[PDB]
Length: 129
Ligand SMILES: [Hg+2]
Image (cartoon, rainbow, N blue to C red; front, side, top):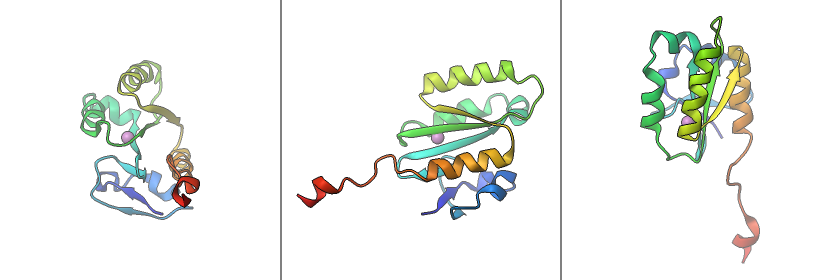
């Protein structure tokens, strides 16, 4: 039921806006575990400028364990277009979904939205047999 949150996310104002599903910190590889094989990384564009090698290593340490991988980018920098195009390339090659959030609140809503769905819900009919 709960979103599991990496302690690396501690202090991220996004957490204030995860309000309609429980969340707790846990020892997890992604920034948010949103189900059995779904997870998200969070990246602020301001942070990305300051630490340009950060996200490539993060996406790479993540690998392919989770079926659905989501990079949630907070667009918080004037003139983000060049950064966004490079992150898009990175996501295409790493096969991850790129989502643009324009505020912490929007990012928190995206997290609750992905948590609403099981990527591989129960399949009862096979089970019954
Ligand atoms: Hg991910």
